[PDB]
Each structure stands twice: as structure tokens, then as C-alpha cells.
Image (cartoon, rainbow, N blue to C red; front, side, top):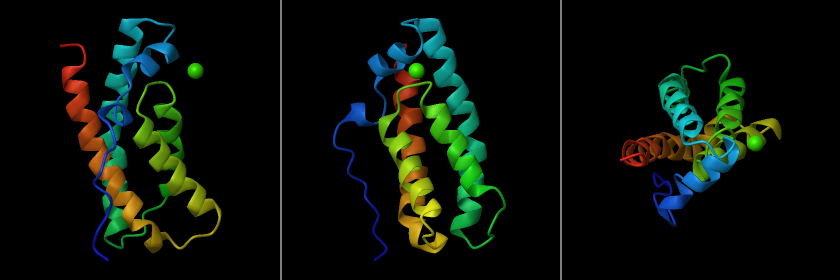
Amino acid sequence: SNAVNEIVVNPNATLDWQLALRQAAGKTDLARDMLQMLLDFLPEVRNKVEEQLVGENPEGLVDLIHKLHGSCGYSGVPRMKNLCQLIEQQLRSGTKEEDLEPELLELLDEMDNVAREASKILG
Ligand SMILES: [Ca+2]
């Protein structure tokens, strides 16, 4: 099927600011900076994921997804973090990379969703 999942069950599945604060010593400034740094990293990941999706077989995909997974842990982006877990764990279990295209497309979508939520959160 061409379809991927576009249902986000609740906007806190995209950005959970109370989770973000809980991971940043309860500090607004640190949670701010960590979210900013995540947003500034996403385009590098987007570009690699797009290359993968069009058959360029880029080097370093799983290691970059792993890095994004870790980065998510410093903030509060549950859907994104879990997408990274799905992608990496499937890749580690030997799944052909082409089979994971739906999750890669969902990750691209979630990058946009996170940016939208991030642009509002501190007002
Ligand atoms: Ca922590």
C-alpha cells in the first residue's frame, strides 16, 4: 500500500513539555535549549532519510537514527523517539531497509509536527 500512518492520537504524543522539563532539571532555559538543538539537528536526519527513501543507500543511516533516538531522550518528543526505536530495532533484527519505508516517511512527517509544536511552546 502507499499509505502510512498519519493519525497522531494526541498532540502530547508529538511534544510533551512536562516530560521535556523533567529531563532538563525542571529548567525552562535548559528545556528550551535542548528543543532548539533537536530542531537544528533534524534537517541532517531528514536529508539522510530522504536519500534512503529514494534508493541512494546512504552510509550511516542506523547510526544517525540512533543518535536522534538519544537526542530525543534529552527532550520530550514521544512519537519521534518511538519511531526511531521502531526503525532501529527493525534494522537491528535484520529487516530489509525497503520494508521500513513507512516508518521513515512517518518520521519525516513527525519532524514537521515537532517543529509546529516547538514554534508555539514558549509563546
Ligand atoms: Ca534523563
